[PDB]
Image (tube, coloured by chain):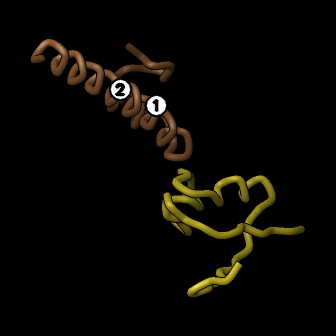
Chain colours: A yellow, B brown
Amino acid sequence: LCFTNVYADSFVIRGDEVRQIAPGQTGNIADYNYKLPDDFTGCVIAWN
Amino acid sequence: SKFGAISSVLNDIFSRLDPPEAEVQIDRLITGRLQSLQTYVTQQLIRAA
């Protein structure tokens, strides 16, 4: 593919807490630290 | 009629479900209701003829 624009975010969280990183989710991270838009397009990447 | 959705009430669906599946459920409901209205209009056109 080719993209009109690209932006990369980064942060550190727990392991099971990565579950909250998805569109329209609710939770401590999803609501009070970092929220993805419901129509977000892209990739979520995490590792130990 | 539920149209296969977990309920026929839009507010309850928006209440107990997250957007990822709430959008699919609402899409099901909207497709069903649009189909019913289209059937109504088609039958009305036949009866109008």
Q: Quadrant of residue B44?
A: top left
**What type is the residue that disc 1 sits on?**
Arg
- Give the camera-side residue of A28 and B8: B8
Query: Is A2 above or below relative to B42?
Result: below
**Residue that appears at 42% across and 20% down:** B7
Location of residue B9 by image quarter: top left
Q: Which residue is mark 2?
A: B35
Q: Secondary structure at mark 1?
A: helix
Quarter of the image where the C terminus of chain B is located: top left
Q: Residue at x 74, y 73 (%)?
A: A12
**On the rendered image, what quadrant is the N terminus of chain B found in?**
top left
Side (left or right) of B23 relative to B8? right
Q: Where is residue B4 drawn, in percent x and y?
A: 50, 19
What's the chain of the residue with tag 2? B
| Subunit bearing disc 1 | B
Other-residue count near label 1 (Cα within 10 Å), few / some / many at <14 / 14–19 / ≥20: some
Q: Residue at x 37, y 33 (%)?
A: B30
Q: Quadrant of residue B41?
A: top left
Q: Amino acid at mark 2?
A: Gln
Instruction: Residue A39: give its label.
Output: none
